[PDB]
Amino acid sequence: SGFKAERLRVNLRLVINRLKLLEKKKTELAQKARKEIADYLAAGKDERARIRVEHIIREDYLVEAMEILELYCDLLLARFGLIQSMKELDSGLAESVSTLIWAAPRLQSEVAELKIVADQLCAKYSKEYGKLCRTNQIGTVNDRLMHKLSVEAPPKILVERYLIEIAKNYNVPYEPDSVVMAEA
Amino acid sequence: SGFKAERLRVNLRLVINRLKLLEKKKTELAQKARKEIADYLAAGKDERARIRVEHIIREDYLVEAMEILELYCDLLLARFGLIQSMKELDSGLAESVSTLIWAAPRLQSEVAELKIVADQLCAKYSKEYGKLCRTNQIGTVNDRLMHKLSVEAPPKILVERYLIEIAKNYNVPYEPDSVVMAEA
Amino acid sequence: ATLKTMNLEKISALMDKFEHQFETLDVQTQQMEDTVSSTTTLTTPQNQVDMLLQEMADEAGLDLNMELPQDELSQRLARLRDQV
Amino acid sequence: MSNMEKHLFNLKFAAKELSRSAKKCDKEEKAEKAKIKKAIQKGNMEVARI
Image (cartoon, rainbow over all chains, first blue to last red; front, side, top):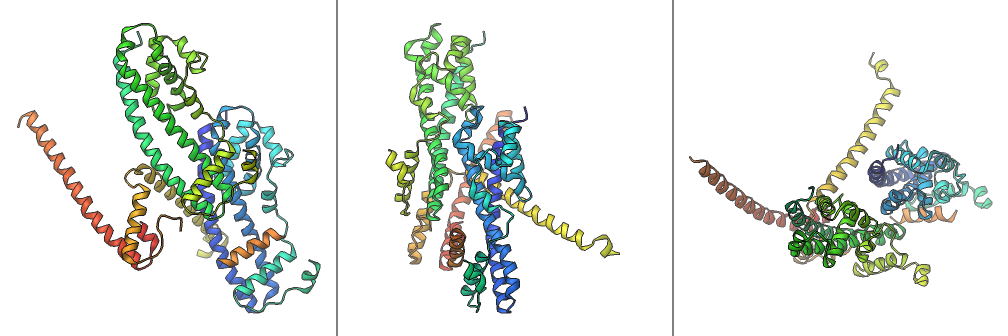
């Protein structure tokens, strides 16, 4: 009881559709954002440009994270026979199932169906496994994805390198923070 | 009682019509899918392309399985005189009858009439024979068909070889997984 | 009166909801079109479309080969993310 | 009109309706082919493919 295979199958397909669409939209919005950084740098407002590129870095990391989750949903669909057949969790699926349960509370603001995918996977493999996933006590959640959805501020050198590349591309004079470039 | 020869004859013909149609449709959809793999490989998203070809391999195996069942339904129609005449199951038909009963629960999502074919064959040769078929305790179900409808993931070398051939055909640069090509 | 009944926080909410509900309608159009596409797969074989495009491109004198699966700032910013 | 004459009248009508539908499809293959050429000349490859 609780678990319904078709709820999981339908919602996995929906999650892929929604992620596939959000990646495109967010990629386009990053173009518009980078133009705005060049405008701030041209206006000599470098100290603000630094804080505006933190938004760009976070959206870029998020788009990369959405690509990883798209892949794990597509993997659970490809090997959906195993999910439905066994009662134990296979090794091949452990990364995917644990990561999707871990990610859902972070992403479910944007990708509402991802909550239902997580809830069904917890109904299948039990609530206790679901709790061990959400904290990564299960030690199986994908490390790169957890990095990409971290709440920490970007490294100062990443911010500076972003400004250097954007400034170069839009032919705007920029001089990077000497202290940060030295610390690197 | 239960068994009606004309229900079986009509539904065997219907099963052939439906399979014959699904094979064509699935073959065409495989063309559209292979183009999509080339697009993923061109975009350098090889790690996803691997998971997308698992869907293609499974549909290709399924089409081959549908061709085997089409042949066994056509065989029971060709030798329908024997089915209707005897009360015992002939040797010549044992493979066909057992395989159709085994396959029905796997396929009856797609081929609804296949359920009725199986139910009639169980009414003819008794429920106990029907149970021995579904588990292949009867040791007569066709091995290639059971392989082709297995829920196991494709071998890694098959996935790599699929990508190599698709990449070559669409003139996309691809470099296969060295570890998998070595393990082979 | 109207700035009370529809204050900026309420407008902010309404605009967020508007945007998010058109994301959902995009997801729905996509899967209606994917269904219709699979529904009429046998009426449009891929190779026939590819050949008609190549024939029309040959007539137009366009060099682009139509059977094949036919920005650098984004690439460089990606390389930066990998390097850190 | 006999009950069978009604059925014959409807079968003859359905046969013509299908024949008209085939003629409409043919004339629209010609119309869409013309639009491919225009889209190729304008470099609109996405519209050409539609």
